[PDB]
Amino acid sequence: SVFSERTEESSAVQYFQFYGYLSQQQNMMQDYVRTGTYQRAILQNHTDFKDKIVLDVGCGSGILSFFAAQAGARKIYAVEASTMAQHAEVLVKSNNLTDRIVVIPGKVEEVSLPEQVDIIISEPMGYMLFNERMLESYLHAKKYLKPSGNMFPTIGDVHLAPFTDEQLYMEQFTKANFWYQPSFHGVDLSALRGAAVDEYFRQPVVDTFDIRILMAKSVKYTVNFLEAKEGDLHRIEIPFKFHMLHSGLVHGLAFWFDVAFIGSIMTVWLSTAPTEPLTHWYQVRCLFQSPLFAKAGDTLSGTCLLIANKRQSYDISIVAQVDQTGSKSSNLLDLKNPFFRYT
Amino acid sequence: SVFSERTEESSAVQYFQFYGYLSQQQNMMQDYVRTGTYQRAILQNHTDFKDKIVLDVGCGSGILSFFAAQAGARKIYAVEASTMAQHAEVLVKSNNLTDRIVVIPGKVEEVSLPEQVDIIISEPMGYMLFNERMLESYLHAKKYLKPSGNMFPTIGDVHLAPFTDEQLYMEQFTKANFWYQPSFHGVDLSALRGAAVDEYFRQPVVDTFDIRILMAKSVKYTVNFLEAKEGDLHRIEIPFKFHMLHSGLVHGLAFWFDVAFIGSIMTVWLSTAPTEPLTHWYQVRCLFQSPLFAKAGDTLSGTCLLIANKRQSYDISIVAQVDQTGSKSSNLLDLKNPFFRYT
Amino acid sequence: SVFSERTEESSAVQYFQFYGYLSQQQNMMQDYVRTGTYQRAILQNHTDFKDKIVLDVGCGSGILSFFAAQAGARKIYAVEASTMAQHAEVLVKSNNLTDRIVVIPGKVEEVSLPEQVDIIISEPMGYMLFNERMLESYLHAKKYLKPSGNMFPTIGDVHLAPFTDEQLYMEQFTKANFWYQPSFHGVDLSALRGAAVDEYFRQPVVDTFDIRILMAKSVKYTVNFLEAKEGDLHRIEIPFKFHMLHSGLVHGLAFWFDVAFIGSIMTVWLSTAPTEPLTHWYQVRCLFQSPLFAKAGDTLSGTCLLIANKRQSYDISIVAQVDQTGSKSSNLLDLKNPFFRYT
Amino acid sequence: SVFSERTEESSAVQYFQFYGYLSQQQNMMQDYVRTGTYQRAILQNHTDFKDKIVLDVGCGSGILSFFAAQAGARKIYAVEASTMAQHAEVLVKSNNLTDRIVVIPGKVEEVSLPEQVDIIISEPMGYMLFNERMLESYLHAKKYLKPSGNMFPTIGDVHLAPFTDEQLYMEQFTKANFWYQPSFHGVDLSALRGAAVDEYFRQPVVDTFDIRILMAKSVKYTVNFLEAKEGDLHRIEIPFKFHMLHSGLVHGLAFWFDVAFIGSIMTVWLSTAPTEPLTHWYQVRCLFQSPLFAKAGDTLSGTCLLIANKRQSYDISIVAQVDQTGSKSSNLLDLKNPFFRYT
Ligand SMILES: Nc1ncnc2c1ncn2[C@@H]1O[C@H](CN(CCCn2cc(C[C@H](N)C(=O)O)nn2)CC[C@H](N)C(=O)O)[C@@H](O)[C@H]1O
Ligand SMILES: Nc1ncnc2c1ncn2[C@@H]1O[C@H](CN(CCCn2cc(C[C@H](N)C(=O)O)nn2)CC[C@H](N)C(=O)O)[C@@H](O)[C@H]1O
Ligand SMILES: Nc1ncnc2c1ncn2[C@@H]1O[C@H](CN(CCCn2cc(C[C@H](N)C(=O)O)nn2)CC[C@H](N)C(=O)O)[C@@H](O)[C@H]1O
Ligand SMILES: Nc1ncnc2c1ncn2[C@@H]1O[C@H](CN(CCCn2cc(C[C@H](N)C(=O)O)nn2)CC[C@H](N)C(=O)O)[C@@H](O)[C@H]1O
């Protein structure tokens, strides 16, 4: 299948085992911004669902399928590959919706649906939008979508902006400096110091922050889920040119995302921006191994390149340069294994 | 190999990727109780190492092999299956010990050693001793041990004791009762409340506690690494008969372990008991599905049965009854997915 | 002469030029602890001066000679090598003490005195006591001292103790990390980071601190000025063994000193300890390039080796070890060019 | 050599020892105005460097030579007399530019260069431009310059302006009045008050100030480095006639400087004016011994005579008079020993 061809079995087992836990579903369901905004997007656009055929990609517990039912959908095919599919069935029965919600266990790339659908609903967004590579499963499912069909969410915006945060930088650098010791219990570790710094700075930092640490207006990269093909997400190149609003040390790039549900009645936005109420997606920051100094008015240019790997994530290459001075920084980050810092 | 036969590839990949991180090695290296006691055990028993041939099973960074070198070992074969073997090799060279420490990348069940060894050193202990099933790799390595060879550690003691902790018990229902609501965004979730409760009770609880919650002297189960066979750890039956020192409700069993390095000069103990300074092993508690009431002087008898699975862990079956009343409780726990509760 | 043979002229020029400024004399005179304690020491032991012959080694403005006059000294030879000798003479005249204070311009190692003296007074103490190597001029002057003659100060105690101050450490490490940049205006500086670290940590830090940063009782090294010869100060070896009172990171050794004026009437102490009111000597700290971890009860052993150089200062070699673990640290410091951090 | 003949050795020793420190090179490098402007001047005039032969006088870390390399220089001679030459060589190697940059240890007046150059680059400016007398080394190097060759910087402007600062003036007496007391610990210090005052007034004051203390537009004295001879800087006579913009008491003259890089594409200016962002050169103020009252519209005329001395500095002689009133004041200052006042 398309899924297995792009996915290490080891990664898939772990991935679907994770979403098989009810405690994990609870955590997502209790993100009221997420759950409430999804419900608002669906119900406020009930005409896009009323008497329509629906596909829910990765239905989990089934909550989005239930929203579609509340909106009057004639039939909802709810696809889920983890064992959570069993629990969704339980809820469909106990909520007397067996006549409209049909759970189909399996990967959306592998199952067979009885008919084409009018609209696909899903929550395929991971950290920094692209983590988990579930967007590709979402786009893949368009093979079941009618020509006049819609997608909820319809588009995704990735925002990136330069930030200054000495404390975060020193916090990570301090960890790596363990490997700087010349005599840990009499053992010289210093030879691995380079490898250590490399390893720690490879971790994106997931948490939230004050918007005042941002040093320039964000750059936006848009994915149109109605137009995009699976293959478009294998290599994502995001060029940027920031016009620095403040002077100081740039310690890296901050990331967040918005998705829009573009319905017939209204467009509803779900935002994970630091200016908005916090979600379980928080925000993501990629540190430079060495900060770049820039003055207000300078331009910070470069590229954020995401290369999809078989562990359902991306290898992230960030190259940034202060155009006026030629000060350049590079880093490779592994989006699969971020550092969860929020407390 | 023996390893691959008892381990699902998926689990093995995840397992050795985990130990491939310098940060994970670091976390263990910074557990001073663990690292310091090993160093003391080896150095204070220098006659067990002086001019001897040593095998280090799962050398990680190589730290224990360096301790063996500090103790005067002639040659140390340091075996490591994760990519950490590369970093260990770097350290052996940078510490000018290539003539005495030989890093051998691969699983100890699969590599070939050039000669027999006088002593095996290792740190194969997981949560409640047996988690990760690395003890079987440690025992397996005895095929390279001379008839008079020693093992560091030499023995392992697992202790179990009944505890009362009303707050821990109730906490499970507080979390599960999330699902006991008739209209979460219009959805009746109550049907899954039972499954949620079950899921929470299947998790052993990793954290520490006040020793005053213990209701009886611990029962001890000893593994003699000099005598035990790999197969002995596939099914571990720990019968118990506790003599209650206090009256109250028993909410489950608490676990911890000790290992002893029985050397020619002295015996050194490494303990993770709740009476001792905390380690990264903390302690482990398994709840009963229903608490058992016992008064001081009563006996709580039953069995803790540990069944090895291919996910490098154990299925835990606990059955207990208050003999004087016949009140009975049981639980089935999955040691692979513990709940890390420590704050 | 003894002075010129041990001193590079360039250093001597700068040295005596420095003390030729009235603003510098003012700065020392306004150290009230210093000035008040000296007057205290001399006047309360007036019997050690009454009708006695006195030598003031490096009289500067002449302040100590005036104290000796106030205490009833019959004749004071005030030796001063800088141009300050001219100003001291002005003060002697304006204070009508020409019959009692005799200024003798020149280095104490070179001038000729008409007679032997009963007591020598001086203020030869520098940073960490020994800086400036004036103690050797003070000891050299005993060639003019009568048998059984006295010296003010009579003895000097150097104290050293291990300290923890993560903030100071990172402050110095941050500065050196400038040379960590791989693209400073497009230039890779990283090749010089080792040299930068070596240079910055070579600087003793002159400032004060809260006594709570000290991790063990101080070790004391005593110089008896009545007994010592100048040659004793060419190589000063200070062994130490600290019994750690607290667990934590040892970032270096803190230094301070006391001198005692052991007179016939009473003993007066001048202390620059952090437990005492601040003087212009403050305290001195020598950082390790990498801190050593120790738990309470451990012993920190090693040697502080001071080698006098021809620049009127010392090359400082510190080697320290946590005995229980073998964790070892070394540093080379240049006492001549300290980092002034206070306020 | 020319250098040794004009420099007392002790001063030279101290001078080049000072610049042998990475921390001092760093301080200059971290002055973004200085470093950024040099880079801009060189790169924006790339036609003046492309395939050219370059001489860098006093290359220090080598930073300006790398800029020349960025601009396309065919070959760069980097001359440095301090031990910093070793570190520059390291950077040349680590930046793979050994084929283009040649580090030459030694004084530019003493080394031998194999060929003539197209352009000389350097940063020889000190306090009030002329301090350190490195400009003479810069001009001396033109013996290696082709007739059609250029100089970067091309010209240097020293600016002078009268200022009022009652607090600064009074400050000198407040400090000197320490000595005006009849019993400092029993000593009459009054006799040295005059000498103390004189001492303070001989020190030019290095710091910055509010431009509002300036009472007239500056007078400019220009040195054209393309035209000037080394000997021109031995005696610098700067006549001035200020047209007073404000009425009040003039307490002295303020100094600052500009340099211009006159390239084929554009002229780039580096300014240390008090109207511009602060640099490590700050500004310099020389007091009159007695203030002069002047009215708006009056003219303050006189001479600032700079006389080079053997300590790589200048004796500053200032004479000024209010023409309309005939009120006259003078001062003689020692630029070698300035008072660093900046807070
Ligand atoms: N190819 C496929 N075929 C069928 N089913 C598939 C599939 N790929 C994934 N799934 C399934 O999709 C579900 C996605 N999950 C939403 C996950 C989005 N997300 C990311 C994060 C943060 C971070 N990335 C993380 O890993 O936690 N939090 N939520 C739950 C959303 C669902 N709508 C719900 O409400 O419960 C999961 O249950 C998963 O098993
Ligand atoms: N069959 C095999 N062949 C070769 N190498 C093998 C192997 N099986 C395991 N290993 C390797 O053994 C190492 C064990 N690890 C110690 C890990 C033990 N541990 C348990 C826990 C408790 C809990 N379960 C947890 O996960 O933290 N924490 N650490 C490091 C020990 C190291 N010598 C040290 O003392 O620093 C790991 O690096 C692992 O890759
Ligand atoms: N061989 C010699 N022959 C003749 N005269 C000599 C001499 N060596 C030094 N001197 C002279 O001795 C004076 C020492 N100075 C006190 C110096 C002690 N000190 C150290 C520091 C801190 C630091 N080490 C520093 O100042 O660099 N501050 N004061 C002043 C002491 C005098 N009692 C006074 O009160 O004014 C200076 O005036 C110096 O010129
Ligand atoms: N005759 C000679 N032959 C060979 N080399 C020589 C020389 N004379 C001086 N030098 C050397 O010239 C260098 C000048 N220095 C710039 C220093 C000038 N400066 C003055 C001030 C102001 C004030 N006077 C102060 O020093 O505080 N700040 N920097 C570094 C400039 C460097 N290229 C840079 O721009 O990064 C120094 O390293 C010095 O050793």
Image (cartoon, coloured by chain):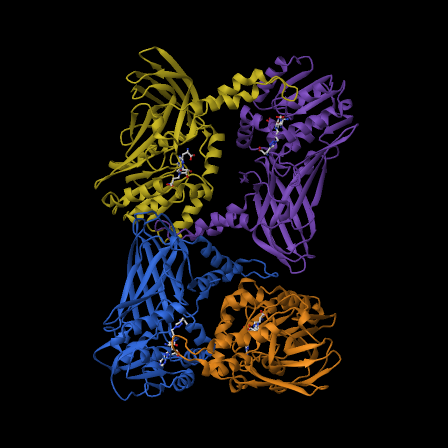
Chain colours: A purple, B yellow, C blue, D orange
Count of numbered circles in the view: 0
Residue A36 appearing in the image: yes
Is D99 on the left or on the right of D217, as rendered? left
Q: In which quarter of the image is the N terminus of chain A?
A: top right
Q: Name the residue: 57% across, 22% down.
A: A84
Give the x, y percent position of residue A187. Answer: 36, 50
Give the x, y percent position of residue D293. Answer: 67, 80
* Residue lying farthest to the left in this orientation: C147
Give the x, y percent position of residue D234. Answer: 60, 86
Q: Quadrant of ligand 3?
A: bottom left
Is C155 on the left or on the right of D70, as rendered? left
Choose between A29 and B57: the one closer to the eye: A29
Residue D147 appearing in the image: no
* Residue lying farthest to the front in this orientation: D182
Give the x, y percent position of residue A325. Answer: 65, 60
Is B52 on the left or on the right of A2, as rendered? left
Q: In this view, does C119 lie above or below A134?
A: below
Q: Is residue D64 above or below residue A303?
A: below
Choose between D230 and D223: the one closer to the eye: D223
Choose between D179 and B263: the one closer to the eye: D179
